[PDB]
Image (cartoon, coloured by chain):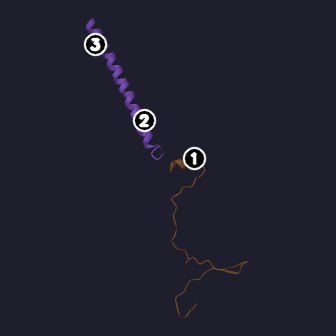
Amino acid sequence: VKYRGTAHGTNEYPFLIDTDGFSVLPVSALGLLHQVHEERIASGVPDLDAMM
Amino acid sequence: LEAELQAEEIALKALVESESAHERQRLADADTLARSRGNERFA
């Protein structure tokens, strides 16, 4: 509600109580920093794989 | 009568040439469609 002295999150964050305890995975922590790879994966269908 | 025979020979040869040309054109069109819908463009 109020954290005096610096910035912070202001939205309502759904949290969970589990065996570990408090767990909070805010949706505002996701970032678009994804290392890409040049390898290819095999679907298992030869025709579909060759189509691309 | 011999003139008639020569005319008929010309007609036969025209028949063969044009028919073979139709064969060739059909093959070419089939190949064009085969590329247009083919996966060989990538491998």
Residue pictured at 28% horizontal, 13% vertical: B7
Mark 3 crowd level (few <14, some 14–19, many ≥20, 10 Å Cα): few
> Residue at coordinates 57% horizontally, 55% vertically from top-left?
A41
Check the residue under mark 2 and report the chain it is in. Answer: B
- Residue A44 place in picture, x, y as percent: 61, 50
Q: Residue furthest left?
A: B3
Chain letter tied to brown: A
Pointer 1 and pointer 3 on the same chain: no
Read off the residue under disc 2: B30
Q: Locate residue B29 relative to residue A31 in the image: left or right.
A: left
The kind of residue tagged 1 is: Pro
Q: Left of B32 or right of it: where is A38?
A: right
Q: Amino acid at mark 2?
A: Ala
Which quadrant, please, contains the N terminus of chain B? Answer: top left
x%, y% of residue B17?
Answer: 34, 22
What crowding class fits label 1: few (fewer than 14 Cα within 10 Å), some (14-19), or many (20 or more)?
Answer: few
Q: Which residue is mark 1?
A: A46
Q: Position of residue A22 (x, y in %)?
A: 68, 81
According to the picture, the residue beneath numbered tag 3 turns out to be: B7
User: Mark 2 or 3 closer to N-term?
Assistant: 3
Percent x, y for residue A2?
57, 92
Tag 1 secondary structure:
helix
Q: Which mark is residue B43?
A: none
